[PDB]
Amino acid sequence: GLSDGEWQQVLNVWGKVEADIAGHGQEVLIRLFTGHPETLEKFDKFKHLKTEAEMKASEDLKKHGTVVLTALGGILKKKGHHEAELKPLAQSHATKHKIPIKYLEFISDAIIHVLHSKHPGDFGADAQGAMTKALELFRNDIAAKYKELGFQ
Ligand code: HEM
Image 1 (tube, rainbow, N blue to C red):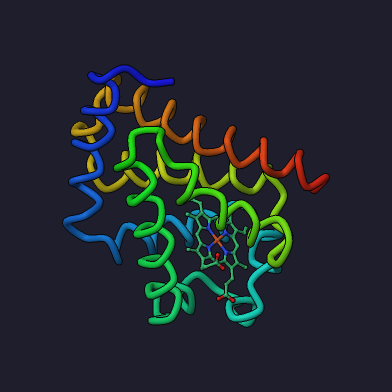
Image 2 (tube, protein in one colour):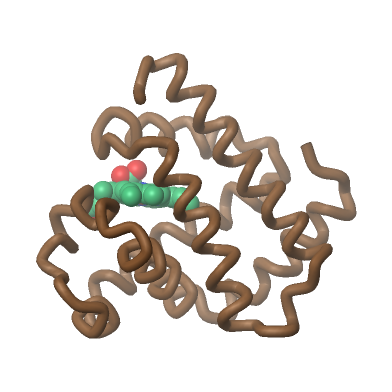
């Protein structure tokens, strides 16, 4: 649950992402894959990537980064009223991709890391607080659907 002022911070930060969605999406996935190499094994189309240089050179990884952040941005713009947008993603990630909630924690922290890396000194403590709360809400509502499905 976020206040109006917190949502305003989230959507202000998101403007930074929308200026370069592919570059942000690429770096988020690279941070996930290099920090948590077990996550790469869930992607049949990226498991061939052995080095970060190959990851950086992969145009399909940048494409998928655009898909991921476009979906997340659509959810964030609903300011919590995201049941219709979130349900299909919860279902596909639990039942088809088999993504444990832990990996959603990993990618949430990766987003925070990338924002500081690309905007050092321009991602203030209030903005980090609000973005963190928004990603916690996203993860918590996914977790509720995971529990319904019995997925661990
Ligand atoms: C912010 C969190 C995430 C968002 C918004 C997101 C979004 C998406 C979307 C929109 C798709 C394509 C449609 C679909 O299959 O539902 C997708 C596919 C997929 N996601 Fe995610 N995802 C997220 C996190 C993760 C994480 C953490 C993992 C694994 C560590 C993951 C694994 C996958 C896989 C394996 C696919 C299929 C890729 C393919 O072969 O095309 N997702 N995701």
